Amino acid sequence: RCNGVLEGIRICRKGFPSRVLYADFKQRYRVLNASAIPEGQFMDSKKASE
Amino acid sequence: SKAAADDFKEAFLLFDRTGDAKITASQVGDIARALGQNPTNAEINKILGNPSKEEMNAAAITFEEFLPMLQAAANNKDQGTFEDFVEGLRVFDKEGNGTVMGAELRHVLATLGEKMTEEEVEELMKGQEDSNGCINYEAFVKHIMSV
Image (cartoon, rainbow over all chains, first blue to last red; front, side):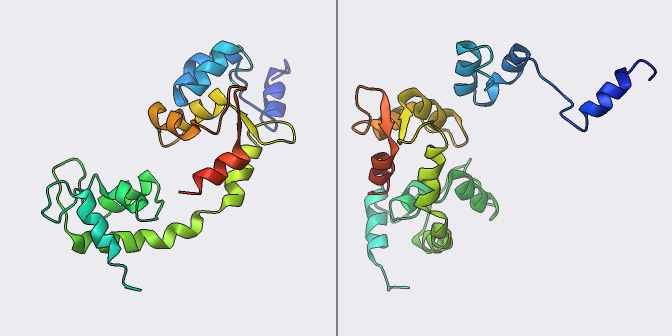
């Protein structure tokens, strides 16, 4: 609390709390539109998730 | 209503392979589309189940159930607006010209939502996409609404 950690989380959550790292994003969710999400993730680690 | 269109009954005799005047429940989706109705496959699925009708076990039909199911699907034809079909694909690719890159439309039509086979996706792009790899969806959606 006194760190600022809990306040950074607050401000985030007002904001955009959860933030996924791209690969961490690919792997876990490729399966959703499997063909088109896998291609995206593989083709550009970032551009993929996009 | 008849306008009693008796050609719906004549088309049921062209889709029944046994000639007994019954059409299985698995053919009813594609025959509603061949009579000039586009209900989504989840809608055709729901209605069926809604009526405690299982498309998992053997099915038969009678004209007396297929006629009112086509008349219940016929009210939903007001959902077929071409403004939203061309604007969907206009938000799918940059710049001021209606062109989808080939593989973008093929992978989206096979894997997003109601799965279309890649055989049917190739049969719907055949002729409208040339060797530049760019599908002009102004003429593509025009020809898709010509059938």
